[PDB]
Amino acid sequence: TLPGTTPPDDNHDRPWWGLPCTVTPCFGARLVQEGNRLHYLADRAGIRGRFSDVDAYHLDQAFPLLMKQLELMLTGGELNPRHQHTVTLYAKGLTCEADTLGSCGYVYLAVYPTPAA
């Protein structure tokens, strides 16, 4: 492509799937939301940086817990597919931000080490 007609920009074929996040390292994902059920797609997620052994272990433990909590929040209404609203969860030393972004079908996540130091 030519920069006059097409200004430089990020490659849209390799986007950040999760919720925008400024912390490093961080795990982002775009979960598929159908009713009160959420689905994690490994190819619709990404990680910036490298989680430490301790934080990686904690992410493994916290992920299922976070998923279950988000599903309950969909069921109860704190997470509404039609309304943008960021919820914050904390688990195993990690912080998780989630938002439907009013996408009517997706739940965007950002998980990173809680800056407790």
Image (spheres, rainbow, N blue to C red):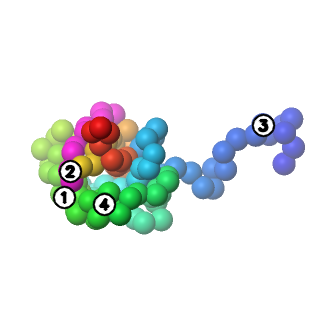
Query: Which segment did they paint magenta?
Result: 80-92
Tags 2 and 3 touching, CB below 8 Å: no
Of pointers 1 and 4, the one earlier in the residue sequence: 4
Instruction: Tell me residue 44's x, y (percent).
Output: 46, 60
- Of helix, strand and loop, which one carries label 2? strand
Badge 4: few (under 14), some or many (20 or more) residues near its Cα, within 10 Å?
few
Q: What crowding class fits label 2: few (fewer than 14 Cα within 10 Å), some (14-19), or many (20 or more)?
A: some
The answer to which of marks 2 and 1 sits earlier in the sequence is 1
Nearest the camera: 83 or 18?
18
Where is residue 114 drawn, in percent x and y? 29, 43
Q: Secondary structure at mark 3?
A: loop
Q: Earlier in the sequence, mark 2 or mark 4?
A: 4
Q: Residues within 10 Å of mark 1 (few under 14, many from 20)?
A: some
Nearer-N-terminus badge (1/3):
3
Residue 61 visible in the current orientation:
yes
| Residue, disc 2 | 91
Which residue in the protein does label 4 denote? 54
Cα gap from disc 2 to disc 3, whole angstroms: 41 Å
Image quarter for residue 14?
bottom right
In the picture of the structure, the residue carrying the numbered disc 1 is 65
For image coordinates 24% across by 49% down, the residue present is 93
Check contact, mark 2 vs mark 1: CB within 8 A: yes
Residue 57 picture location, percent across and down: 29, 64
Q: Secondary structure at mark 1?
A: helix
Q: Amino acid at mark 3?
A: Pro
For the question of whether residue 82 can be seen, the reply is: no
Seen at 19% across and 58% down, the residue is 65
Give left or right: position of 106 versus 73.
Answer: right
Percent across and percent down for residue 73 are 17, 46
Quadrant assignment, res 23: top left
